[PDB]
Amino acid sequence: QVCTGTDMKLRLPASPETHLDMLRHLYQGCQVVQGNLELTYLPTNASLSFLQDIQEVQGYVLIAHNQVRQVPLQRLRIVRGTQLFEDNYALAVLDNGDPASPGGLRELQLRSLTEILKGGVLIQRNPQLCYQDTILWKDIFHKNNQLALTLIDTNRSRACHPCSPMCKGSRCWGESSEDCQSLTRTVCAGGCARCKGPLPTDCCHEQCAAGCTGPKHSDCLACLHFNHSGICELHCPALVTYNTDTFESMPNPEGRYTFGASCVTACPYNYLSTDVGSCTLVCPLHNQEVTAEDGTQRCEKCPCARVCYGLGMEHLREVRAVTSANIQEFAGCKKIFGSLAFLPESFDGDPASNTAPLQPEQLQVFETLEEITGYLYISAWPDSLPDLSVFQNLQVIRGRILHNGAYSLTLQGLGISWLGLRSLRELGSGLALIHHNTHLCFVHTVPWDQLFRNPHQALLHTANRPEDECVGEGLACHQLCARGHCWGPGPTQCVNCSQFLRGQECVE
Image (cartoon, rainbow, N blue to C red; front, side):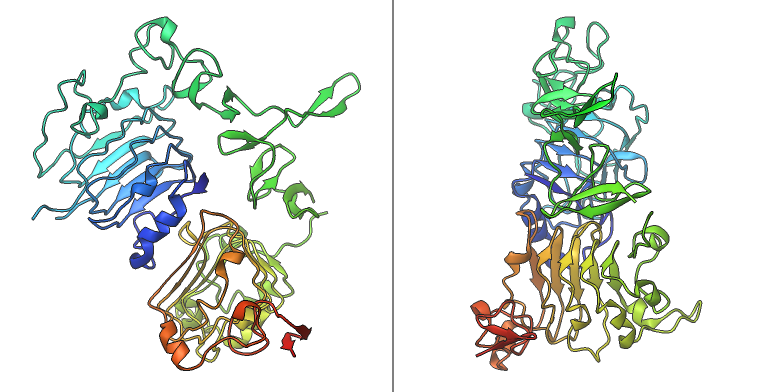
């Protein structure tokens, strides 16, 4: 029921062909989206009904380059705006249409949208879109959301029918009466931030956001800060309380962690329990990730060990791929904190600095790697390597950082005949995508679902070597493989053995 969005922005999907299923797998059944919610480059005939469940977005909401006439986000109530589009917009709609009926967005239909916590609104170049200019946006922007930008492009090729006659003030998201925007902020008697009506008795509890059922902290539709079992509070109750005469620690049975905008009893899988009582993915400076014997993580004081970092972290924040100039940074690593990527640039080198192209022996630095905290993206690989076995010892991909905010594992355009990633056991989060891997077999010979740890993640694949061809050539799994499942040819590539093992070999 809770999932994250992506970070593709206005960039084309790596595999547009599977993009709609990606969204389907990610969002069907998801009420709350962490991070930003982005729908970009979707076709006219896309079916997006799986988005009908979304109620809240932690970050910004972006609709762009879609030819989609309708986007079923009418249930959305609040945009929290942790990140803004172009650092300014909580919500933005761009280029959703064509230059038989034309494609492009016609209505927003955000009838349940009541609030923008922070950030403005940007609507541009959407020639088929109506009523973007009727919404009394100042009523939606939070009281303290003074970045009340309304960059609304009203240049439309499509004529707009007036808003249903039942809409007071003709403020609507679409023609229907149901698409009329209720005014609940600038119309409140008593001067309260939010209300249900013209009376002061209609005022929402002061700790409430995006509207209410009443004046109590137990009467809100969405909390300003945290939702503790339906109760709105500034913060989650402390995990430990104190007797200040002696400063005795008293773990609080009612104490909760802060995650998202709600209170939890424990951090979600792959999240770390901080000393703060917050759930993170990344520890504060001078704290380290510690894994408990029960498999969960926490941030604890570190004194501090040298830590191996990947792309997206520390001095590698600006680095897009591992280059030949970065290899030594992984020497001696078992766990890398960050992402890795092997893109043509890695293998082309860098004429601006005359960096040599990455050689296959330099990838040996990763043979000792057991865990990556970020994502792995390969779009280029030496053709001398028939597989990705240099990472055969990689057991865990956590997906803390996702490629374009979506993938924890992506492989594309490769000549590898098999993956060979025999140690992989878990894909902690994120999507996996295999595409255009012209010569790659053993795609459906892997019980892929066994390494997925969430209903909101799945393996997507397209245009790879057809299994039909792999089958015709006998690129089948060894008869001693559990379930007939493997990562590549031979007794050593089995996901598990039905037999005794000798080294990597299933033997009988």
